[PDB]
Amino acid sequence: SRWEFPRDGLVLGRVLGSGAFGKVVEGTAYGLSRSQPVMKVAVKMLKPTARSSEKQALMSELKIMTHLGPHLNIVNLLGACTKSGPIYIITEYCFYGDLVNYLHKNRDSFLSNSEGLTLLDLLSFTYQVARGMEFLASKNCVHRDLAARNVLLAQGKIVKICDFGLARDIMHDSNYVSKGSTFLPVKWMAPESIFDNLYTTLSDVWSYGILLWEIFSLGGTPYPGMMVDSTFYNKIKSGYRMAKPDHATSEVYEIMVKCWNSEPEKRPSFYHLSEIVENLLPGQY
Ligand SMILES: Cc1ccc(NC(=O)c2ccc(CN(CCN(C)C)C(=O)c3cccnc3)cc2)cc1Nc1nccc(-c2cccnc2)n1
Ligand SMILES: [Cl-]
Ligand SMILES: [Cl-]
Ligand SMILES: [Cl-]
């Protein structure tokens, strides 16, 4: 495969995330970049605890990444090690890490700029996520776990959608609730995913609305203070929706409301979301 990179071209680093069978670590790649002899990357791999279902899953993820091709707002595949060893997937490294912790870090200095984040930045993140999801939708790729924790931020404030997957400890993460044999991100899920096991680009649009709530609360937990229990499920069914977060404009909140239509087909497309948000950007962008 043309994606193949020699394993001995890597020096492995500090762990960036781990779950039960997988992890992602920082690494240095020699001779991988054509313009840079030495470069920092991120590498995904399995732990010795991993079984065939995991190895299969990681190979399947590599295949989907190659098939999708590149996009500015999707974490960028750089290579892989699949022969004569445990499988590694290599991507770009993103300077600021995940969007949740970045927003939290930025709470004190929020200005609404080198001095801190503004509404413009929040709208930029909103727009870039929509573009990334528009790209995935155009390849018929349904994300199923869209959330700010699965958005990375590169040094130029460029959003990169990912899915930690096996490199997140879903069994020990309050964002994932036991619902069957696995843990699911219930507070981000569309009702038809919760109740009917239906996942589509339209359920990704619901999750996108929840992600916007995360952005405009500077990394708040959706449905703050609400446990996922029978009362939660009844509330969603009865039509309960989150109120506008403090840094959102009325137009941004209108967008979240649209994304949370009970009927999936009534939710707006990621194409239209991208165009609408772009139109909300101020002149200096
Ligand atoms: C190394 C590394 C290896 C692999 C990946 N690959 C993915 O995350 C991934 C790619 C494609 C897909 C495919 N699917 C369909 C399947 N799902 C329905 C299951 C999507 O829906 C989809 C498509 C496209 C995007 N997101 C979701 C799923 C997951 C990322 C990283 N990098 C990575 N990962 C985590 C953290 C960092 C990090 C941390 C801190 C600083 N700097 C960097 N970097
Ligand atoms: Cl760095
Ligand atoms: Cl239920
Ligand atoms: Cl808020």
Image (cartoon, rainbow, N blue to C red):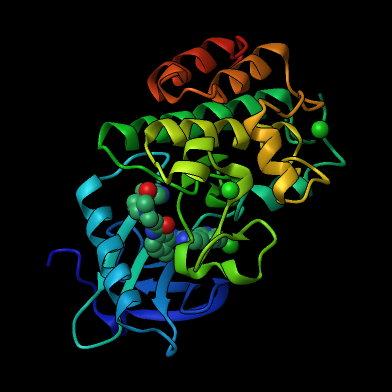
Q: In this view, does 37 lie above or below 100?
A: below
- Asked if residue 74 shows in the view, the reply is yes
Q: How many marks?
A: 0
Q: Residue furthest right?
A: 108
Q: Tell me what residue is drawn at x 13 percent, y 64 percent.
A: 2
- Asked if residue 40 shows in the view, the reply is no
Place of residue 245 in the rendered image (x, y in percent of width and height, measured from the top left): 78, 27
Place of residue 231 in the rendered image (x, y in percent of width and height, measured from the top left): 75, 43
Q: In this view, does 51 lie above or below 266?
A: below
Along the line of sight, the residue nearer the viewer: 277 or 194:
194
Place of residue 192 in the rendered image (x, y in percent of width and height, measured from the top left): 47, 37
Along the line of sight, the residue nearer the viewer: 190 or 219:
190
Q: Tell me what residue is drawn at x 26 percent, y 63 percent.
A: 60
In which quadrant of the rendered view does residue 90 lie?
A: bottom left
Along the line of sight, the residue nearer the viewer: 41 or 186:
186
Image quadrant of ligand 2 equals: bottom right
Q: Tell me what residue is drawn at x 28 percent, y 54 percent.
A: 65
Identify the image quadrant of the C terminus: top right
Q: Tell me what residue is drawn at x 57 percent, y 25 percent.
A: 260
Place of residue 193 in the rendered image (x, y in percent of width and height, measured from the top left): 47, 42
Q: Which residue lies furthest to the left in this view?
A: 1
